[PDB]
Image (cartoon, grey):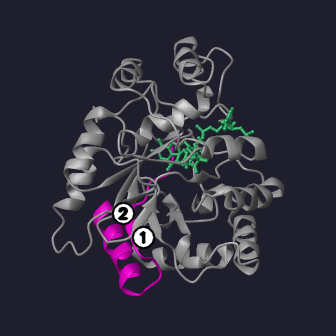
Amino acid sequence: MASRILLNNGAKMPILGLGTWKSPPGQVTEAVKVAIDVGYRHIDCAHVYQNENEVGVAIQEKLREQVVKREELFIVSKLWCTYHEKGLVKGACQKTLSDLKLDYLDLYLIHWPTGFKPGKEFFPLDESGNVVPSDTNILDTWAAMEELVDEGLVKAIGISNFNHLQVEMILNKPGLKYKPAVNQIECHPYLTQEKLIQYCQSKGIVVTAYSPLGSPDRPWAKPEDPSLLEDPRIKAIAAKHNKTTAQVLIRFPMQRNLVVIPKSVTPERIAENFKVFDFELSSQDMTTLLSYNRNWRVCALLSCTSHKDYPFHEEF
Ligand SMILES: NC(=O)C1=CN([C@@H]2O[C@H](COP(=O)(O)OP(=O)(O)OC[C@H]3O[C@@H](n4cnc5c(N)ncnc54)[C@H](OP(=O)(O)O)[C@@H]3O)[C@@H](O)[C@H]2O)C=CC1
Ligand SMILES: O=C(O)Cn1cc(Cc2nc3c(F)c(F)cc(F)c3s2)c2ccccc21
């Protein structure tokens, strides 16, 4: 297994990256520096995570130390929902570039298909708790994303949390210039996504699996919720291979030809999570892990379910 997957712009994307959602600003600089030292080359960022400046400090130090060159890193960020209007997309990208202290991004994603009212709040709500939409549609935001490629700010563009009809809408866009390179979606043994992943891969779109460990630090976790890291069936597969449960959960998507982006701020775990290139799950193990699907989705907010472009009413 090769460590990088070819995208439809001819660039190679590392199949393992470091996630940064919920990584506190006081701890994420060290986390990214340790990750680069132990071999990570792909970092997944977003403006809404409120820590891009601190991620940028780490990247800049390791470029200055000559640990890595810029061309070896693969830096991803995402356009938040309050910037879907075509005249706001460039300025949102440039704020992220300014915080990360970079002159281009390797990949820039539409974070969610839903546009929200522009303003200071990331989740503008009405008096009854519903998100306030904007009158934007995904095709005009896509055309604004394409302009960032032509201006040299980003090397590739893609999408996140799009269902297959929303992907189809972009693929059928009048005058489509650049196809989405990536769809970043939730994927783990309790939400295996078979139909959407085969949809995407058949279309030449690479899939990145987010929350591969089930996001145990998500703020809305409840004590009664399932835990992938503690599932005794997954523990038994790990023990057979003399690996940890997290290492099996990271290797699983890699063998489906997915990119995977586990988050940690703990140095030991950052190093553990990288040590996944020296074993293989058997075909039988893969089919068994797929059988654990329960259509259990952890990233989906009730306040967004009446939005016209909410992605998760459709089957896939
Ligand atoms: N596009 C989108 O809408 C979304 C994108 N994402 C991206 O995907 C990334 C990963 O998903 P995320 O939801 O953060 O959750 P993960 O599934 O990656 O789980 C992160 C949690 O697992 C813990 N952990 C990490 N490694 C280990 C290990 N070896 N052993 C035990 N526990 C471990 C972490 O603890 P600790 O940090 O304390 O070590 C943290 O509590 C995000 O950070 C973000 O970059 C996620 C959700 C949505
Ligand atoms: O987004 C991240 O990366 C991490 N991340 C994930 C969620 C849950 C969402 N669920 C939805 C949703 F169903 C929508 F339709 C639109 C939307 F914008 C959200 S956001 C979230 C909520 C607050 C901050 C980060 C969050």
Task: Specify the segment rendered in magenta.
Answer: 130-158
Q: Is residue 136 magenta?
A: yes
Q: Secondary structure at mark 2?
A: loop
Q: Badge 2, how many Cα within 10 Å: few under 14, some, many 20+?
A: some
User: Looking at this rendering, what residue extends furthest in the front direction?
Assistant: 278
Quarter of the image with the C terminus is: top left
Task: State the separation of the CA atoms marked 2 and 1.
Answer: 6 Å
Q: Badge 1, how many Cα within 10 Å: few under 14, some, many 20+?
A: many
Residue 72 vs 189, above or below: the answer is below
Residue 136 is labelled as 2
Residues at badges 2 and 1 in contact (C-beta under 8 Å)? yes
**Residue in the picture at 43% in, 42% down:** 254
- Pointer 2 or 1: first along the chain: 1
Looking at the picture, how far across and down is residue 170, in whole percent?
Answer: 24, 60
The residue beneath circle 1 is 85
Residue 278 vs 234, above or below: the answer is below
Question: What amino acid is labelled 2 in the image?
Answer: Thr
Foreground residue among 305 and 177 = 177
Foreground residue among 177 and 73 = 73
Residue 113 shows in this picture = no
Q: Is residue 268 left or right of residue 73?
A: right
